[PDB]
Image 1 (cartoon, helix red, strand yellow):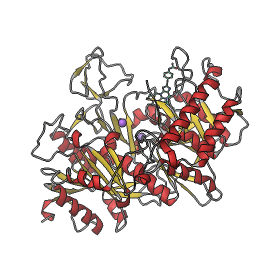
Image 2 (cartoon, rainbow, N blue to C red):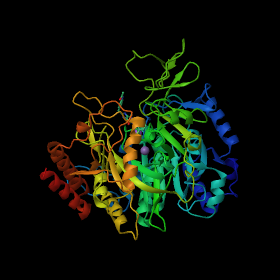
Image 3 (cartoon, rainbow, N blue to C red):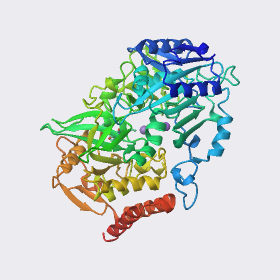
Image 4 (tube, rainbow, N blue to C red):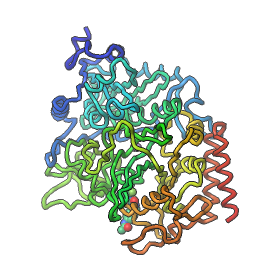
Length: 605
Ligand SMILES: CCCCn1c(=O)n(Cc2ccccc2F)c(=O)c2[nH]c(Cc3ccc(NC(C)=O)cc3)nc21
Ligand SMILES: [Mn+2]
Ligand code: NA
């Protein structure tokens, strides 16, 4: 009866709990066929070919095995306003704010979710194939790795999941009869189609809903096929669900790149960094450093799972298998390693296409050859006078991590890499120096808590996790604070960076990019106890002449590193207001103390 629908694999080979998850949802969604993914190259080639037929993907003939998907303009991004966590008690998910609506999460009652679920999923896959994606977050078989099963009616999701996760039969074999996170996804357009189909990309914007049910170990997503909404291992699983598990089991699931940096003497450290959007996070993750003798290597560009080892060192793994990177602004100058990575075996979404089957986007910094023309992401002839970008601002490459020329040798080690420094950062046109260092662990947690960044609007994004907290942010802060009482903890040094400070004409004070190796150099030596410190009210900055400026043009170091009482009076008042308002009864006393200490330090300047 159900075996009759199966077009690849066998129900009898699946572990019982996987079979039952499949059976329950096939009955609910009523797909025409079941395809159990094996993750093989042969399967991938076949789905691409099928997606090419149906106009889902176009071949990019300039490259080896590269493909382009164009979406419905209504479905172009991860959508927070349609994203919820479902728990019995609201407080477990989000703090009750003093005023307004919480910006720290979006809670939906179990009752409300059942209704919303029943209004969407029954019969949602009629006319489509349900794909069964067995995937591992983290190196196959590792202590810190977790496995999920994603059922989807989207072949784009399957092919993207193959890159972004370890996917297929080896995962089922590692899983056996173990636990897994249940992931259910549908584009929400059963056949026959009730509504027009734009660029062969099905979506249901009106009913779009991305839900998390932590107690059930379930992620349920409806109506969007795009990145953060559909690739369920990434944000939904590896950040939201995982951060909750992390708090319960004593580890951390964080929105952090991980890189390894080696000095000219062969000494190597691993660093983690959390940035909000529009900060060049991926660029830093695979930075080509300007300083002679230095090496930078990439562990991951988005997510880090961290746990104390037996000697109290924080060990990170990258739970992803690829990079889901923003395309526009990617060039040989801004990210030479990302450019090499994406030359082959890569899926691009919503970028432009050149007439010779290449890709294009704003800031690609690549002059077109004579007679080459550009088709935009809206399938229109494009010119620079059109007054709209050739690529969507949120357009993507989706690319294997193994292909990064500077992929770290330990990027898949099951034991993880030891983190010696955590870097918080933002885009701040005024007031905030290029780099500073936390005064203590408690102060460091507060620095993460206080993060704000220019999106012409400056908004708060604490730990870069604001859209991603799996649970009460107040409890998340308490969890971070508790790391200082972990026996023999070797706590990472905490820093804050701003690449984006401007002079009064809005010119950037710091050249940045590969020159940010100089800032990493200072952090590196600080971790090693170098007396390169000068104390300020906000933390330590580099002493006079301590930052390595050899080979640079003139830098206005005085403005770059200036700390104004006026600016910081306003800053701390804004930080206090936001944290007391938003975190309310759940704000740890250690953070209250750091807010007041900063105020006192500022008042004395
Ligand atoms: C979302 C787009 C972010 C782009 N981006 C950016 O991505 N990084 C981060 C970064 C890039 C490459 C390597 C490492 C790294 F950390 C910067 O340091 C940076 N500075 C700046 C501002 C800047 C600074 C200087 C200049 N030009 C000149 C001549 O100085 C142009 C722009 N943009 C950066
Ligand atoms: Mn991210
Ligand atoms: Na987005």
